[PDB]
């Protein structure tokens, strides 16, 4: 499957792509404002994520740090990134269909549109100014808007027991972005697409 990753932000981002225990494609790359990077994701990939990272420094070996979404200090991510990270999430070729969503469960850093480039389903978007409107207690000093689990480490926010409800914090993310997951047991906003669809992830779509 192809994923075209487009940075429409006025600032550089370092795109990342992983399934948690492995890179997808090269795993990460710099995208200056306006740049597009097309990756190949193996059919059947389950639990893949794409995100942006901000305010990164890398040495000539590809080692360094980002202020949001850092993946073990690597340019080429092999693992998931440090919150806050707006997440484009997907599982491909799962009994004949693909499943896509955007999640704010691990916070928000950069606005995102995640849409098919092929027929048969709709895209999803979270492009509201979540950083600017972020509740004070959720603001990440390093940049972005943290989820409540990251900040407070409670069973209720982290849904540890598999019993949790919406919270004042989850409802903030849901109000700004109805079409993204705001907490673990949110009513799903997952879109079913034809198996083997292709996609575009646009940072700063609006």
Image (cartoon, rainbow, N blue to C red):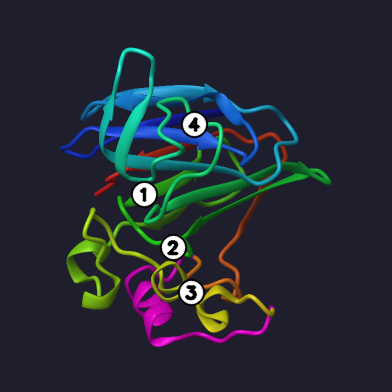
Residue sitting at 34 percent across and 40 percent down?
53
Identify the disc placed on residue 180.
none
Does residue 103 belong to the magenta stretch? Answer: no
Residue found farthest to the right: 95
Q: Residues within 10 Å of mark 3 (few under 14, many from 20)?
A: few
Mark toward the start of the polypeptide (2 vs 4): 4
174 is within the stretch colored magenta: yes
Residue wearing tag 2: 104
Which residue is tagged 1?
112
Label number found at residue 153:
3
The tag earlier along the polypeptide, 4 or 1, is 4
CB atoms of marks 1 and 2 within 8 Å: no
* Residue 117 at least partly seen: no
Dot 3 or dot 4: first in sequence order is 4
- Tag 1's secondary structure? strand
Above/below status of 94 relative to 13: below
Q: Nearer the viewer, mark 3 or mark 2?
A: 3
Task: Give, as a single range, the part of the protein colored magenta.
Answer: 162-180
Q: Where does residue 139 sit, x and y in percent of width and height?
A: 25, 67
Q: Quadrant of the N terminus?
A: top right
Which residue carries the number 4 mark? Answer: 77
Locate residue 2 relative to residue 91 in the image: left or right: left
Question: Which element is circle 3 on?
Answer: loop
């Amino acid at each position: 499957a192809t994923f075209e990753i487009v940075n429409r932000c006025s600032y550089t981002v370092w795109a990342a792509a992983s399934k948690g225990d492995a890179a997808l494609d090269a795993g990460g790359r710099q995208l200056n404002s306006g740049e597009s990077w097309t990756i190949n994701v193996e059919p059947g990939t389950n639990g893949g994520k794409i995100w942006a990272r901000t305010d990164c420094y890398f040495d000539d070996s590809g080692s360094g740090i980002c202020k949001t979404g850092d993946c073990g200090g690597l340019l080429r991510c092999k693992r998931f990134g440090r919150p806050p990270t707006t997440l484009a999430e997907f599982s491909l070729n799962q009994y004949g269909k693909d499943y896509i969503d955007i999640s704010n469960i691990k916070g928000f850093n950069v606005p995102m549109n995640f849409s098919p480039t092929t027929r048969g389903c709709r895209g999803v978007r979270c492009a509201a100014d979540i950083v600017g409107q972020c509740p004070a207690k959720l603001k990440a000093p390093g940049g972005g808007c943290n989820d409540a689990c990251t900040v407070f480490q409670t069973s209720e926010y982290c849904c540890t027991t598999g019993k949790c409800g919406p919270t004042e914090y989850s409802r903030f993310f849901k109000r700004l972005c109805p079409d993204a997951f705001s907490y673990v047991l949110d009513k799903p906003t997952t879109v079913t697409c034809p198996g083997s669809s292709n996609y575009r992830v646009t940072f700063c779509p609006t």
